[PDB]
Structures are given as structure tokens and as C-alpha cells.
Length: 236
Ligand SMILES: [Cl-]
Ligand SMILES: [Fe+2]
Ligand SMILES: [Mg+2]
Image 1: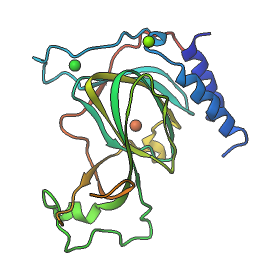
Image 2: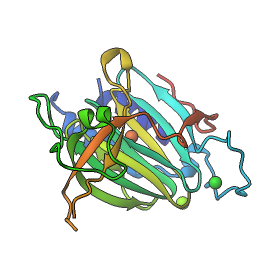
Image 3: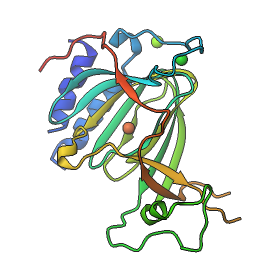
Image 4: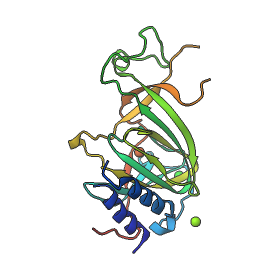
């Protein structure tokens, strides 16, 4: 069986904390470490002649397989693009770079269910906050920023750690195979929401670093469309 098919089988077994989950997650990570662009029939892509249409998607998605337990697919970023900061509520995540370089910034929202965690009213922000914006801004933590190439191992996130991240293409196009479990499902309250860091105007700090996060629609210059998957087909 192809590698992508064995990834799907192991993912199905891994995602259905149950007994044996940590060992299964380890086996899945080992399989993803092995994945190469050619295993998916994808050739690495270089920058397009940048007289590019404004209707051209900055990012595209190849669907491979999705169940109630997990989703498996490939995101392909054009030059100079990014998948902006977003969350994966109650989800595990695991991705492997296929070509190019991406910068992955990892953050977490602090739990604010108990209330009263708005910024100090006297604190001011770069592009000042609208009243509705300030009412919604909540604290978070910037945990890491790192560059990943096809030689790097998988980048992994859990429901409770590194659950927010941004993925920027560095010095050219890039692509990664992504596994999410459970998949996004608005019907179950698992929305793919976007966030923007707001910078306070009060005259640096090492990571981990306190940040202020605001839920927002994705940036105007970002959207993702599907394109055909050319690799080995995955079956049940
Ligand atoms: Cl490009
Ligand atoms: Fe993500
Ligand atoms: Mg190679």
C-alpha cells in the first residue's frame, strides 16, 4: 500500500485520552516524517511570473480523505502568501512540509471564561481599537516562531498547546500535508476562526510572550480554493 494510504489507515486508528493513543500518535508522526512531495505526485512549485490575476487564490487545497474522525489534505501556498493566524478548537494537528519553507508562529489563547480579562482601559494600541474591538480583545501567549523545510520533521499541535498558529511562505512557494482530528465542524462548535495580534502603544521580551488577540474575519488578501489532488487515492 502507498504511504498516503497507510497514513490514512493509521490516522483512522489513532483518531476515533483513550489507551494506546500516545503510541498511535507516535506511529502516525513517524509515517508523516517519511512523506515526500513525490509520494503525492506533486512536483515542487516555484514562483509564478508575478503579473498575476487579483482573482488568483493565494492558497489552494488538495483534498485527500476525510472522515468523522480526521481530515487529510495538502495546502499549497504561493509566493509571499500566508495562512493567517487561526485556531483548531479541541483538535489535534500535524503537518509536514513537502517543498519550500514556511514560518510557523504558535500561540495559545488564555482561558478567559471567568471574565474580566480585557486590556487596561487606559492602555492604547497601534491603529487604536474600535470600541467593539477592545470589548472583544483577550490575552494570549506567543510561544514560538520557527521555520520548517521538507527536511524538518512534522509540526504538531494539541487542543491545549500551540492551538493557534500562522503559516507564512518564506522566499517562495511552499506546500504541506495537513492532518486535523477531529475535522473542523461548525455544527459541533469547532469553527476555523481567525485572530489578529494587537500591539499596545506603551514604551524587547523573549518568548513566551504575552500578546493581545482579537477574533476577526480573515484578511482581505487571504482565501483558499480547492484544486485537484493528483496522488494515490485513499480508500476506506
Ligand atoms: Cl507564486
Ligand atoms: Fe492550521
Ligand atoms: Mg526529495
